Image 1 (cartoon, one colour):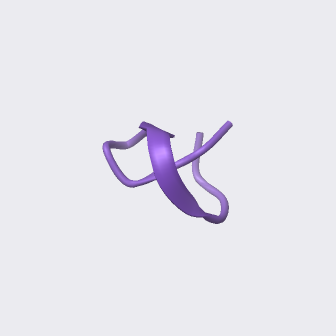
Image 2: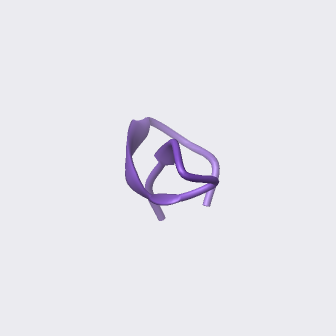
Length: 15
């Protein structure tokens, strides 16, 4: 769910 970085979508971003 492309946006700020993390660990919940695109193996990179968060919802």
